[PDB]
Image (cartoon, rainbow, N blue to C red; front, side, top):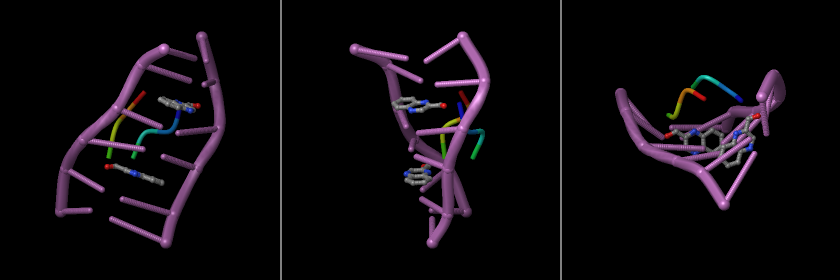
Length: 8
DNA sequence: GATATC
DNA sequence: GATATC
Ligand SMILES: *C(=O)c1cnc2ccccc2n1
Ligand SMILES: *C(=O)c1cnc2ccccc2n1
């Protein structure tokens, strides 16, 4: 759920 | 480092 | 299960 390097 | 909503 | 980036 975090949106950092992936954004899910 | 830099992590939480589906 | 469902994950990558400066
Ligand atoms: C988002 O809350 C979150 C938490 N754990 C994960 C594990 C693997 C892929 C994506 C994820 N997203
Ligand atoms: C993004 O590429 C990425 C990869 N690994 C992580 C681990 C912990 C927090 C954030 C992250 N972001």
